[PDB]
Image (spheres, rainbow, N blue to C red):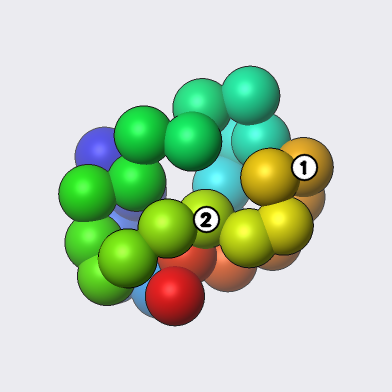
Amino acid sequence: CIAHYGKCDGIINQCCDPWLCTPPIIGFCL
């Protein structure tokens, strides 16, 4: 579910760690 500090698809806000994916469109989970 998105590696630590990994890129996110956007539609999938299910980011286990570290916290949440932002922006909800395209960015990095922090």
Q: Which residue is mark 2?
A: 21
Could one spot residue 6 in this view of the protein?
no
Quadrant position of the N terminus in the picture: top left
**At which x and y percent is residue 5?**
40, 73
Q: Is residue 6 left or right of residue 10?
A: left
Q: Quadrant of residue 7?
A: bottom right
Q: Residue at coordinates 66% horizontally, 35% vertically from top-left?
A: 10
Circle 1 — which element?
loop
Disc 1 marks a residue whose amino acid type is Ile
Q: Position of residue 28 (x, y in %)?
A: 58, 66
Position of 9 with respect to 1 (left or right) is: right
Residue type marked 2: Cys
Q: Residues within 10 Å of mark 1 (few under 14, many from 20)?
A: few
Residue under the point 24% across and 61% down:
17
Q: Residue 25: which numbered mark, if any?
A: 1
In the rendered view, does 7 fall on the left or right side of 1?
right
Q: Secondary structure at mark 2?
A: strand
Q: Indicate the quadrant where residue 25 lies.
A: top right
Pointer 2: residues within 10 angstroms few (<14), some, or many (20+)?
many
